[PDB]
Image (cartoon, rainbow, N blue to C red; front, side, top):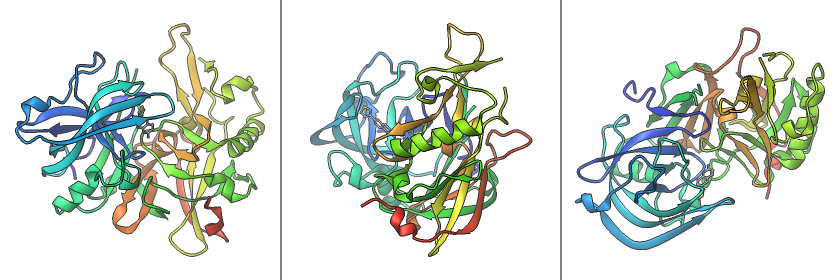
Length: 375
Ligand SMILES: Nc1ccc2cc(-c3ccsc3)ccc2n1
């Protein structure tokens, strides 16, 4: 897996991408790695923000599926033409597979003006593929057509500053993490859904009905930046973070992500956040702990300010909990599809000081963990 280490690149706030090839001869494309969706979809027309795009006319192995796909999101959309072709990952396993590909022919607020990627690799399950679950996602195709084991893992390292990481396809690289992996079950194979059973700020329990933590979902998502929390949970978490960091006060807007706060930096004033996840065994949980250096993100994009402005990277949501980069950059994350589970271990590349560290600890006893799932 040494050939796969450090195969992820990107710019701060613009996602992680991996080099891929599509068609014959191979066409090189940078593709966003997204555990939050299930479509392999690439730009196929000269959108002026794109460095490169899939040219179907140049591929001898392209096959038309004679079907369109329309994908709206909250903000905008993407739209495309479904087909198949041969796909490779130059810094992945030495294999070539026939995969479904959405050729994107129209988009709005999908591509990022200024980024170095031209497509998306949805790593989640068939159930949330567009237009329906008959469209087999890339990873399913990879496992069916080769001996590549049914798992992948992600080390997202963070630092517009350049970001880096590793996607290890088909296994686990033990030098990307310290301590032991701890596994939480995949509750259902659609998103990577898991169950949060307890939340603490600075070891202080939030004491909420644990069903609020997973209302209506909790998911692991490499395609989101923030730790997103349901509004009711976010409201309590914010109140508790504010009380923990009394030493200095901040306007309501900052906590709401409506404005930035700037220095010329004190980490100790801010609390650690702990999430307890359902463990592998009846009545057993474990906890993941992140620092302010994960949830307080630098903004370098500030043109009207030559100070160190930060964004509060926890926000409200109506789609459930989203464990985004705020969480994932603390940990080596194993997506163990073979055994319907997700593993977490302290990341060897995570940003920390000399007083506190990201942590993965257990076992703990936690009763009635079933009840924390929304139905
Ligand atoms: N993990 C995520 C989060 C947000 C996403 C939004 C889009 C999209 C589609 C049409 S416009 C924007 C696609 C994939 C996404 N994956």
